[PDB]
Amino acid sequence: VGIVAAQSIGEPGTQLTMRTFHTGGVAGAADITQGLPRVIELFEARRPKAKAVISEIDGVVRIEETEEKLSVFVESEGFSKEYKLPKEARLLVKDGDYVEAGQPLTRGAIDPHQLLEAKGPEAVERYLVEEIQKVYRAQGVKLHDKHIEIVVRQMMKYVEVTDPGDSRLLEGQVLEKWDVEALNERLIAEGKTPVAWKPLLMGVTKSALSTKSWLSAASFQNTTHVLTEAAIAGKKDELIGLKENVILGRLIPAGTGSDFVRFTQVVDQKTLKAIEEAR
Amino acid sequence: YQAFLRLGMEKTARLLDALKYYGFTFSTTSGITIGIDDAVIPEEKKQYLEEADRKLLQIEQAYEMGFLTDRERYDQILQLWTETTEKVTQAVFKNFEENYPFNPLYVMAQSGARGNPQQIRQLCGLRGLMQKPSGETFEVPVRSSFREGLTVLEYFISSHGARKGGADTALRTADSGYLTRKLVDVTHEIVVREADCGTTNYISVPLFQPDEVTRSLRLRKRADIEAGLYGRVLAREVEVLGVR
Amino acid sequence: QGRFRQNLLGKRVDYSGRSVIVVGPQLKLHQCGLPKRMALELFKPFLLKKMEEKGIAPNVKAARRMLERQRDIKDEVWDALEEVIHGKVVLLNRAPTLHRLGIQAFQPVLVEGQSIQLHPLVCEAFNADFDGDQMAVHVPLSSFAQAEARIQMLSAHNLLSPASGEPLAKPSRDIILGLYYIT
Amino acid sequence: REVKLTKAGYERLMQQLERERERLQEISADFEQALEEGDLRENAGYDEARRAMWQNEARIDSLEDILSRAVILEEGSGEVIGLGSVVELEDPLSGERLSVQVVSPAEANVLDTPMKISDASPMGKALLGHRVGDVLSLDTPKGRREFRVVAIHG
Amino acid sequence: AEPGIDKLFGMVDSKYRLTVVVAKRAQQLLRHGFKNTVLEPEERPKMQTLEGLFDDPNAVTWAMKELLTGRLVFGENLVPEDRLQKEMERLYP
Amino acid sequence: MEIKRFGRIREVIPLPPLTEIQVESYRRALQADVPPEKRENVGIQAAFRETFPIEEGLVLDFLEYRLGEPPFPQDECREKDLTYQAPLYARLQLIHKDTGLIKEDEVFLGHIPLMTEDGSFIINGADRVIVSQIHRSPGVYFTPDPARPGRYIASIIPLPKRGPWIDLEVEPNGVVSMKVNKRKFPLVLLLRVLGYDQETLARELGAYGELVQGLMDESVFAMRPEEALIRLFTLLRPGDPPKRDKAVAYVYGLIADPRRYDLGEAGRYKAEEKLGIRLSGRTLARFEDGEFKDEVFLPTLRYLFALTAGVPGHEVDDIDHLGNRRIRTVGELMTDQFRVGLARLARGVRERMLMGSEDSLTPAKLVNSRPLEAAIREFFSRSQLSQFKDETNPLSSLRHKRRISALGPGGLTRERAGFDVRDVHRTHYGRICPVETPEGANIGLITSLAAYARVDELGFIRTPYRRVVGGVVTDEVVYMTATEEDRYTIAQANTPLEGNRIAAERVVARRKGEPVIVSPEEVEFMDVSPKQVFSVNTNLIPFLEHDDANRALMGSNMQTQAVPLIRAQAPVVMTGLEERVVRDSLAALYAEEDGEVAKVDGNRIVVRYEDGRLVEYPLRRFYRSNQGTALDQRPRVVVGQRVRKGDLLADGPASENGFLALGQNVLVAIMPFDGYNFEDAIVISEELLKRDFYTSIHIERYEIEARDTKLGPERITRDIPHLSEAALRDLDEEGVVRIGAEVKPGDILVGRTSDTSLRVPPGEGGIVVRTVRLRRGDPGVELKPGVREVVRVYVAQKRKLQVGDKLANRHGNKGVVAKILPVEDMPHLPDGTPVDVILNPLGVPSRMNLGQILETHLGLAGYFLGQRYISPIFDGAKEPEIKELLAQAFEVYFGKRKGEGFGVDKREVEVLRRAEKLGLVTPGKTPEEQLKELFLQGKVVLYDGRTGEPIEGPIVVGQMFIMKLYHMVEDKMHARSTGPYSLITQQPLGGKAQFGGQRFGEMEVWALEAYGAAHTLQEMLTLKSDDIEGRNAAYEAIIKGEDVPEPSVPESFRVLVKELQALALDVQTLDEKDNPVDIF
Ligand SMILES: [Mg+2]
């Protein structure tokens, strides 16, 4: 599937541009960065051109027109979240209306990290998938969401440590690995030693950069450092994953070489009983 | 698509093979080709041309007295042609639609064959307005039909785009699947292997789109919907349209 | 160009074949044309083996010299070549490969000309038109690699683009033209 | 700020976005073909059509932009030319008569019954603030002709 | 397309399963001599100018045709590993 | 054959020398045609006066320059890899401060190449080209500030590359800024260095610009005259002594830095014209009397406060505007590099005075060709400018002969900043063909010059224009500058005319680069012709007026890739330039003067001029083209024949009767076939391949040199260490292969020793035609060091169009050749005569290029009328006239059918029957007329031939002009299986007896990975490459009829394991349950 995702998306990539003239009173050339460039930034947690400041707080809305800098408050329970937006900025949310956490205050693009903290993980992910499609959709590209989803999945396959229990609180490990602990934390071994984890969003590149297997790291990243630190500890490289198992030249973990069918039986009645005749 | 989902793989092929043959076979006996006269120019030509001729003069007579601003005259005129051209368009199709339902050029476009409406215009009808080197489209439209001898300058103008078109196609095909590269660098170790995951965590797939023109929930386009539900695994069974 | 980043960037392969491409109307999607000259050289080894099963040549090298240089390639030789492939199928590859179908399996068959005959339906698949382009052709020597080559790489088996449930064997221009002028 | 429009002007503009949606959708379709059309690199058709997208993609923005923050005027009563009034200029010496209805910069269209002039237009500038009986001029390529506001109705 | 390819996919629990199965039996057909077939009587694969395709045509071409008939049986752990080439080489010349 | 041209416009002045771009440019550059008496200046001479007056006392100046004695003739240099130069001598004398001596001994310094009759150069055995280049004529220009819509910014740039980039930025916070070498400083300071005093300054300056207080500010420093300079230096980053080291300053005096360009135009232009007035000196110079005068700073600023204030005349110069963009012709480029060597030469003479041994030296002591010659050789062979002369055919070279590009020395245009210049600008009008640019990247960066358009005294491509008084057209014209053009109102040449006066009142014209409608009263000028609008490359298209600029661009370049077919045929339709082309192109040779024919030998042509004289002409039989092709000259005259001055003697490579003929005019029946003409596929009748219609001649130059290693020099001889005689037969001579021999892939042409014999590389070779060697006794050849001798082998063969052949039309419709159906079952016309080529209509719509559809029809009549036509670009034939003649043709096709005694055919019935039901024919009319009326549309009945059943519905037919391209099937035919291997790594690379399998790339693999073809993939990464074990292991199994080997461990696996072991890395291979695993 991996390759799939990659192909289905790669192919189109070589047909996306755009950025011309009809606008020009400030630093606006399109209203954001529509085209292939957007795809990058999306696949790579960045701060878009027309970032719309969101309100991590959920309340109402109040504005103050003209005079130096306009301001909009997201008051509610008691506190008032002030956001200073230049008079040359445009917003969609109007006075009064109720706003939720991680809501597009300004008109344009959103910010990855910001949306994450405010609303949460689930929101970001859904944002991404859709945000991508938008691009390919406005280009006559009809690709199933499946693929896009797989991608982003890895952009969150890693979280950070908050509460110790076996490793420092300054580390970021594989999301699944956390379950390897979450389970042995209370099930196998008693004494519940929680490990508050917080999923970390990473762009495609950075993601691979933090791969688990060393074999892979030995390719992309600086070989030296890799093997180096990988040596210190008796790092165990499970030969699972095209990339790494590719270097070795060994049969790829997928396809016909898959661990599921790699072992098949092709018996013929004429000899099937012959196995019974050996007992 | 239906065939495949019905009969089966192989069978589909045979269909395709059969089609291919017949397609060509008739495409030869049909007796269809392209001739200078096959690019019939709707008589409405001379009509609309005048309808838009004195029309423009009207807006001009206005600004000459200071009625419209320097910018208005620009957007105004543009509207004229942008739309006056849309007219001639549908016009031509009509003439073929009623008189020559078998006219070569025509049949092509309509049929799932080649040819595109927008393109046809630049033949029977005539190209609209081109763009200036900067970005803002030109002011003097292309009152000439491809089927007819396009004047010198108008050609010089129609080149502003030919050069531009070959410009973007040089900066997007150079990197050659650069994306895929980086993309694969993270999906190269993702493959199927299991027997039904235990995670009962469903996914919320929107059937309706948020705001487009005021906070009003609308139904997302047909395509998008499929691109998200077509072939999936319904977590919680749900009987809606009366079907289980 | 080190060692770790070596097995990745791949390299040159044997039994490689390529040339100008042309449409193959008569050809069935179940197969693909292929210049006799090429198939022959691109199959020197295999050929030789069958050359033995026949009184063509006494032993291996015997057949090697038999055609080491012959402007009169025995009529028997040819018939044998075809008798060599039989079911075995080769592979086709466009230069810019971005999608999986950038390479599909086909059952080659003796053909004239010096260019490779390719089916029109796959034209859409491997982004390429008949203006002068040129595809590639490999041959699954491994009787095991030959399996998955025609089992999961065969063209007639790859119609539904994984990218989208949209058909790939979508009739084009000419075909349509007729199918419409008739209905 | 706040774009000012009229019921009539609204119906024409709102409907405009509706027409453009039927067109724009046709643009995307054309591409879904060109991309599958084979022929690489120069579909004369491809690029020109691409820009065409930006053009509709753009008109879609300018349209939906104003439509989300506009107003509505019912200036059927009053004497001073306001937003929605239909004034009538009559060249003094000529004795010729005319009719017009100036409106906000988002209504410009010489086609309407009373030639709808932009609010920020020189013509729209010298009319606001004066009433029945006024006579003024501005700058004109052919010279400078003054006009007396015959009568302001509605 | 290929002969009853569909009927095949329906016999396997996974597309890739088929492949590995077709390949394994394909070899055993040539290495362990070409007389391990089960459909040799009639309807056996044939050639052209000379229907001599009754002895050695193409491996897989036969393998699948064998699966065409529910004569054979497959699985993950059907018969002991090593007990494979032992019962085969002794039963066939 | 008959010749009818529809020329309505009176083409006044004919097309100028299409090669004068390179011609005169070299001429005037190096005034050599006339003695030093005719003291010109510019170029060579000017170069002397420049860095010649040398004084360190060293006192040596220029006297006379002469030379031009080419060591070997043309051809000689080509075949002998020699350099077509010319011994360059120089006459100069020396005078001392101590009155005396006048030593003037002929001193020469290196040789210089020369320009060929065609306008090319023969550097080292090969013919190259010196392409022109564009840029921004080094002058004064004002353009708006970067991202600040505030004020604007002035700019001064006096080339050569040794000219400082000075800029004037108006810093709002206060004071004006002068950018130089990445540093800003108060211009005031400098002004003071010039003598400008506070009072005299401000007054005559900011008398209108209150902003003046932004420079009249200095009341502390601007109070010190000459002292200012001391300070100015303090600005220079370097920490040098504040003494009289006024170096950097003086640098910007009158020496090199400030452009030393012509005192009147080159510089004065951007001067007088834009700002200031007169040009004191040649640039912002004058460093005499200690002080400095610069009537440059005053203006540049006087213009600044001007635009930043009132309206002295709206001076906001435009970039792309050609009226400020200069060209760099061969002469300029060359003379430029020349000055380089001069400055480098003078470098020595100066130092060779400090160490000079008194007045006992002058010539050699101060001269050395080393510096000079070095430069020249660098430009003509190391500069990216010079290139491989594209001789794919006559036309091709011509285009590459007059093309232009932006990229170059760098100090003009870079590579990552020009999306602006790439687009066609308003000024390009009639100056640069908008459809002459190449495809792919760099598009726009490189594009030839227009037609009539010609270069001026200094770049600035002018263009012809018709003068007009009121409504009367003047027969006089002048080349207007891209600048002064906008000054007037020009009208089109389309404009109807009545003898010498305008027609309709509503006339079309272009005001200031803007399309406008003006009355016959404001007509200041008029277009000379539609031609001057585009370049030749395009002026060859039939009905351009009916094809998109995009698709036109295609056919335009396509003609350049045409192949010199043997049976040349002039296009059924011609733009009328074919005659001129073959002329200035020098593809064919014309008679110098009037006289009579003498010897008409297939190799030599002799004639006796009327002025009492006799001369013969070498007939280059079959010369090896630079792109591998034929270059013969077919004598189109006969023994004893009165000829006129400038008459067709022998045809060019692709010429025929003085008319260009790049291809053939074959019958065409556009219509969909059995899919054989799918995408762009092109069917074809064997009939054509029969009468050797589409075919050409190809050549292959394989060279071999007898190296001289220190392990025993290699000897050329029939000595073959493998006692092979079955291959030494054809190898008659002692090493070289016989002439006229039929070499085949693998045979030997030359025998090397140490056995490194030069065999016949993969593919083919053809039949040898001519070969020559070069022993030790070099009669006069520059045998490369370490080389004992050299040999060449000119082989060739015929290119008979087969299957993989591709051919396009002048309209840009390219397509391969699928099947070639025989004339037997080929769609035929009711009366015999089958078709020739079948094109698929589907390639007409999407591709808006109706032009073809036109040429066809027009050609459909030329077949029966038996004639050819010439249609001007836009003034070409019109729909009406055509139908007239075409109809006349019908009275010939069917007109004969009548008298012969036969009418219509039962088949012709059914077809016309559906014709009427298709609205093609007017019902009620008689068959006769029905067919006629239908013939006028360009469509006719047509029988299948395969089944005899005609195709219901007429099929537009005619004679379209096509042609084969350079790209053949020879350079593509890799068929490998078993062969060599990478001596270094382990890759199946061939080259000799076998070939090399194409690469696989990670891309293809991925897709392979997707499929899940684990084995198929693993097979490609090992058994077919690296791991040599499994490779052979596999070969055996195959030849043995056994299953292919299944690699247990790729050599890459185990090698890496230990490769890491080699350094710490305790790579331990564990099994499924943490257990050892034997690797080897
Ligand atoms: Mg192509």
Image (tube, grey):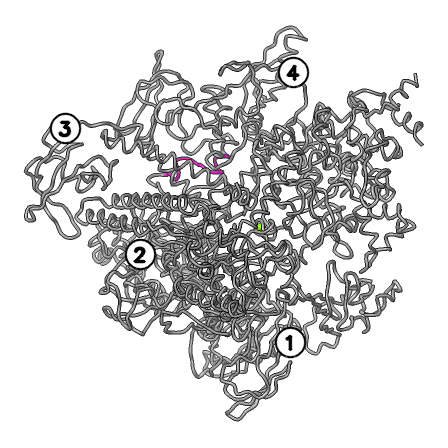
Residue F343 in view: no
**Which element is circle 1 on?**
loop
> Are the two marked residues, 2 and 4, in contact with CB atoms closer than 8 angstroms?
no
Residue F51 lies left or right of residue F691; in this view the side is left
Nearer to us in this view, A179 or F433: F433
Q: Amino acid at mark 4?
A: Val
Q: Which residue is mark 3?
A: D76
Which amino acid type is marked by label 1? Arg
Picture coordinates of residue B216 (x, y %)? 37, 22
The kind of residue on which mark 3 rests is Gly
Residue F901: x %, y % from top left: 54, 68
Of circles 1 and 3, the one toward us is 3
**What separation in Å lies between label 2 and label 1 (alpha carbons)?**
53 Å
Q: Nearer the viewer, mark 1 or mark 4?
A: 1
* SS assignment at label 4: helix
State the separation of the CA atoms marked 1 and 4: 85 Å
Q: Which residues are magenta?
A: A27-40
Chain bearing mark 2: F
Both labels 4 and 3 in a single chain: no
Nearest to the eye among marks 2 and 1: give it: 1
The residue lying at 56 percent from left, 18 percent from top is B234
Residue F811 in the image, given as x and y percentages of width and height? 49, 58
**Residue position for label 2:** F514
Q: Earlier in the sequence, mark 2 or mark 1?
A: 2
